[PDB]
Image 1: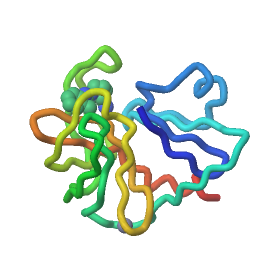
Image 2: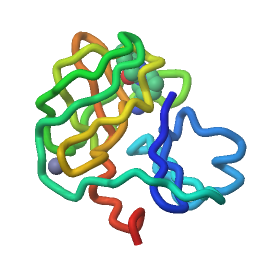
Image 3: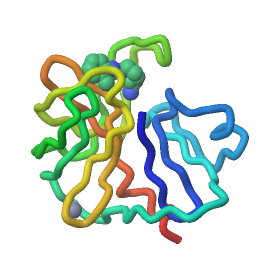
Image 4: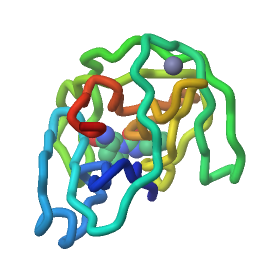
Length: 139
Ligand SMILES: Cc1ccccc1NC(=O)N1CCC[C@H](C(N)=O)C1
Ligand SMILES: [Zn+2]
């Protein structure tokens, strides 16, 4: 679990979104595992607007933050789950690090702010859904 709260928006993994999130839908993309819904309160998260490839992420299965080197957003093959069939997830950035299924939602951050959230993992790897290209979140 986990979300980004920026301005009048809540950004979550599409596979974990609630009824409320779908009732207050702004935008959704199955191919990125992202969903954005509207909130009546103000979000104070700063979204990074950069090309960084190092940062820190929250790993709830270890209750620890880990520094990571991560790849550029790309189309990466993701195995079948009860949420999606086998497919290419776009805007995904991998790193060597610990992750477990309940880890999705954990924020990845650099010096510039929120980079994205945990979306994939396994085999000693962790994948983050990038949000730096969604410029409309701040305006
Ligand atoms: C997060 C994780 C870590 C270690 C082991 C397994 C996982 N589970 C996953 O990768 N996913 C399950 C839920 C949906 C995900 C997606 N973006 O399609 C894929
Ligand atoms: Zn940055």
